[PDB]
Structures are given as C-alpha cells and as structure tokens.
Length: 154
Length: 154
Image 1: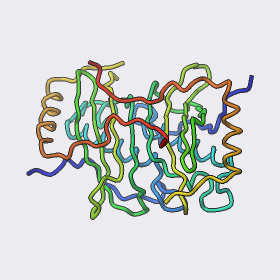
Image 2 (image 1 turned 180 degrees about the vertical axis):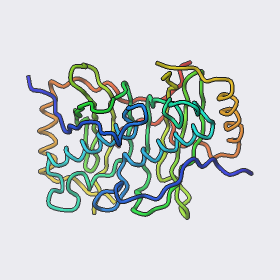
Image 3 (image 1 turned 30 degrees about the vertical axis):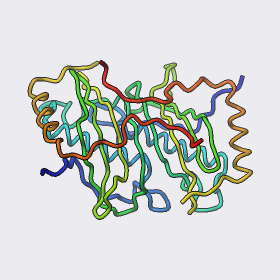
Image 4 (image 1 turned 30 degrees about the horizontal axis):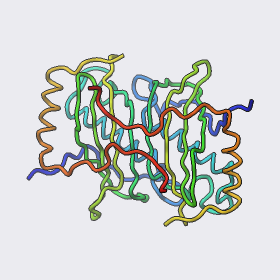
C-alpha cells in the first residue's frame, strides 16, 4: 500500500512567524506554492524553458482552510493530490502535515492555468505523467476541504 | 461621496516575483495579511499587548481569486471591507488595485478568529470602531468574489 505523494518539506523559519511564533497565514500558502513548483519539476513541465518549475502556471483561484497553528521550528511537509485537469488547467489539493500529529494542519484546493510564455495546451507527455500520478492516488485519503465556502456561525 | 478604505500600500519587490517578473500567488495573500494587520492597528485591537497589529487574529479560512498578473515594481494598494462580525470572528474582503486600471487585480474573502493570548470576545470599544467602519461602506463597490467555489470548465 503505497505512501502518499510528498512534494515539499521545510522547517518553519523565523521570518515566517508573528511575534508569538506562529506561522502567518500567507506563508502556509507560500509552502504550498513551492509544493506546486516541485510538482511541476516532478512531471518535467516546461523543464527546458523559463516556464520550468511552476513558472508557466498562473494560479487562478485557491481556497485555504487553516486547522492548526504552526510554531517556529516545526518540520512540515506537503501532500499533494491531482483532482482533475483539462487541456490547460490543473485542479490540485495540498495538505500540510507534521510528525506525530495525525490530522492536517492546513489544506488548500487550487486551480492553476498553464500559460504560454495567454494559455497553452498540455502536451501528450505531460498528460501521461499526470495520469501516472493520478493512478497512484487509489490509496490516498479523500480530500476533505473541497468546495468550501465561508460563513459566520449562525 | 467618500473614498474606499485603503489599508495597505506597497511596491512589488524582486523577492516576491518569479523568473518572469510576476508576483507569486502566495505574496498576493501576504500583501492582504499585512492589510489585515493594518486594519487591526486602525481599530486599535489589542494595541497595548502582544496581540497588537493582527497578532491576536488567527485566519480560519480564505478564498482568493487572481484576476491579473502583477509585475515587478508595480505600486499596489489594498481596499478592505468588513462583511460581518460576531462575538469573536471577523468576516473581511480585501481587493488589490493599481493606478490606471479600473478592475481588481485580485480579491480575497476571509474569516478570522480573535484568540486569547483558544478564542476571546471583542470588547465594546472594538465593536464600536467596527460599526463605525461598516457605516462608512455605504458607497463602496459590492464585493464581487464572495461565496466562490472551484471547478474545471465543463
């Protein structure tokens, strides 16, 4: 039973935390952005041009749920699932994790556009690598924080 | 007819952009985070403690729509509306703008929790300042990017 896809690991640094030592909201999203870039390295998307490493993707839209504070020095990693894709868009879900705590710290659903240099289609090879990764998701935990909308409690 | 509330202004710096000179997705959210902090300075929330300047707020959840790329050196500002609040939560909407272009570059709906030092109620004075700001929103453009959900085009 194969482990989840981990795309990115880092240690929370002092320039990402507030006075009280908690990871600022935007820097959870930064860690996920770096994860998106690493996912593009893995599938070699536009690897030989300035579009490499996520540079050819424009994030259209993202939701993020923050379930837990993350303190200075915490070692964290990102898990990433591909929810869907079409000729030029990728639908992805990142979750943030740490050792010894078995629920997500944060999760984000995102839609990304492949852009020319104005959008550009995914080539046959990219599609094949995306399908390969997707096939390897049969064991993954289903994405919880999907289709989310904000409201004050009644 | 009174102008919109501007909470934050900055110039996009080289450490926020990708190889192609475009603002990375997470750094739109960083600019909005700083805007949230400045909003808390304006209403003086926990001004005399380590909770000052947004430190006593935990972002629970956020959506962000990215309508336009933002290039290196662009002077941008944030507009902020208070959509609602209860005893301990603030519902806010930030939009990103630049001179000479009259649609939003990006927008984000967020829900934030006031936390003790575990949550804490807003005091009478905070509520009065929040109501004052809200009253000044009669002229504001209605928030467009609300209740948004992600989907691939059919």
